[PDB]
Length: 123
Image: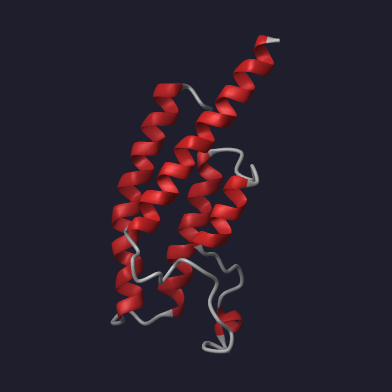
């Protein structure tokens, strides 16, 4: 049916958009600060303060497994990455400043992705 065709087209187009967003976000982090989960050997107290850890590898795994229903769910995981980094690290640190940089750049990319969801009619 055409309802199935439209649903499958919205799924594949949202996936294409989210993959482009995630690639642009990762390209802005060549130091790989947000690429992978934090090592508990290097940071033993991380889970004493961060209850819901998040990183770009976890997001990519969720994206490619069809785990994001809409752009808002993807935005929530990106905000978790930024917020956890700003909560764990003191403000006068290279890691907190990297989160502020990615929050600036990421906000612009995500608002452009919202304009594309609206233009395409994805949600």
